Amino acid sequence: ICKGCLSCSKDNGCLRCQPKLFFYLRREGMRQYGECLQSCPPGYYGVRGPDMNRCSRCRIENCDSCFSRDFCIKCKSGFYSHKGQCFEECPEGFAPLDDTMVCVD
Amino acid sequence: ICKGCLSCSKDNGCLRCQPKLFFYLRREGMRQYGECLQSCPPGYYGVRGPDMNRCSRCRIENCDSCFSRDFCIKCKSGFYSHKGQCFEECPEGFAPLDDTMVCVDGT
Amino acid sequence: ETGESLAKETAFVEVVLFESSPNGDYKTHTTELQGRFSRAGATISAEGEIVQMHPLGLCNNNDEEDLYEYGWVGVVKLEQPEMDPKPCLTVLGKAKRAVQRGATAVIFDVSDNPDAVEQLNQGLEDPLKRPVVYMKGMDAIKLMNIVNKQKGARARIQHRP
Amino acid sequence: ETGESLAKETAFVEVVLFESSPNGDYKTHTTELQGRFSRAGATISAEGEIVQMHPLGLCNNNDEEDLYEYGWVGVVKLEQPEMDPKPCLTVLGKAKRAVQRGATAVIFDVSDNPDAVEQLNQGLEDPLKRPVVYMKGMDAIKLMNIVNKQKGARARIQHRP
């Protein structure tokens, strides 16, 4: 049944979440329904909007976990993190800090 | 272009093949056009019909190579062949011959 | 002083459930529903696979969204107005956004938000080129039952001239 | 004795090419073409993704044929009749077979086989419940060019009396 929502609908799932939680839109074939989660699922990051908290799909190139739309926190293996984006090699101007995968100056 | 066809059109490719070749229908996005091949592609078997030689898709369960719609020549690795079909284990009353994938009566 | 508006034309919506059958053929079964064409969109026939959209997901705010195949018919079940106290978009806005995301047409179930009908029909904004249909009552119940329970379905929205 | 035939109604066929953005939005670009509704099918609007079918592929034979998503618009370019000396099916039969296999409409390019029109409009067989449209000339050349060169396209067949 309707875990985490203050209001729920048989057709649309959750409409508002208890205020801790994140609103996630689950796609199941033709259906799209709302769920309220403690944390966003893999591949998704959370956004605390003015109205509600919600999950959105990470689409940063060569990222394994997004903070926000344009800021990757964990790049995928072999790419260096540079100002929220993931590169095969650091860009000129920066090198990796010692044994790690962060570009620095 | 029109390779192997007796007749050909821009929009349909081959309409008729040179007599030895097999007629295969290639799907490329919205397109579907005729090709005339010496042998049908992987996944397909050839049928010499009354009018034309065609390629048809092998749909036999767990078969890597069809002879016809209903008869498999090469089962997928790890499957046993019996009467043109492919089984994980030889059906009741049959056993693999020697160290092969062919079912014969026994054990 | 203005008089009553012309009635909105009937949208005859055929919902098709389809099933592949022995050979590669399809067995189909049709349900006939009725709604109305709103002034928010053109009065024309449209057809496409049915895709439910949660009303709260139709926003400009959330930006990169998943790519759906072009030409789907959006089904949006509207909730009681107070459930969305400051909408990201008006009902016309949401319909537009669905069309931007490739909708060939949009059907709103307005059973729980009768006021949406006045909004759709205001006719102050310039209409979409695709149909924006509203439905309610048993028609809407039958539509949502299919969406909730079937694997797939195609809507054929017919303008019967 | 029987007189002339009522002229067949015009099918207005919008061919829609679309493009997606990174954000998940689509732009569309439409070409409007014209054909006619034959008696072999209904005179109604239909819409779906365009799929070319080679005439030789529409048979009862080749039995294990592939599976396309329900609701496609078949485009069949007919060749000169001597190019298929013993057809597996008549032109009506081919239209029926496309509908069996999920087509929402069939458009025949009859430029190279104008006698197909007469056969389509005979009205002896039970007509299909989907439109069976025929096109030729400039319009057919344009359709077949889009099929041949572009990646995907959607057809919108409109009946406007």
Image (spheres, coloured by chain):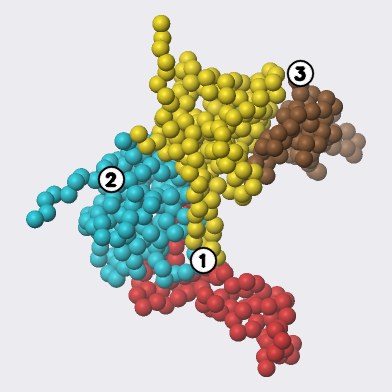
Chain colours: A red, B brown, C cyan, D yellow
Look at the image and tell me whether residue B45 can be seen.
no
Report the amino acid beneath label 2.
Answer: Arg
Both labels 3 and 1 in a single chain: no
Disc 3 to disc 2, C-alpha distance: 55 Å
Q: Which mark is residue C36?
A: 2
Q: Chain of mark 2?
A: C
Secondary structure, mark 3, is loop
**Residue shown at the point (36%, 61%) measured from the top left:** C94
Residue D129 or residue D42, whichever sits in front: D42
Report the amino acid beneath label 3.
Answer: Pro
Q: Residue furthest left?
A: C1
**Residue shown at the point (74%, 32%) measured from the top left:** B8
User: Badge 2 local density, few (<14 within 10 Å), some, or many (20+)?
Assistant: many
User: Badge 3 local density, few (<14 within 10 Å), some, or many (20+)?
Assistant: few
Horizontally, is A33 left or right of C4 in the view? right
**Residue shown at the point (40%, 21%) measured from the top left:** D6
Disc 3 to disc 1, C-alpha distance: 54 Å
D75 over A50 or under it: above or below? above
Residue C45 in the image: state x and y as whole percent. Answer: 38, 42
Where is the C terminus of chain C found, in terms of image quarters? top left
Q: Chain of mark 3?
A: B
Residue A100 in the image: state x and y as whole percent. Answer: 71, 86
Which residue is the site of mark 1?
D23
Q: Residue furthest top?
A: D1
Look at the image and tell me whether residue A49 can be seen.
yes
Where is the N terminus of chain C found, in terms of image quarters? bottom left
Residue B99 in the image: state x and y as whole percent. Answer: 90, 39
Which residue is the site of mark 3?
B50
Report the amino acid beneath label 1.
Answer: Asn
Secondary structure, mark 2, is strand
Q: Residue furthest right?
A: B98
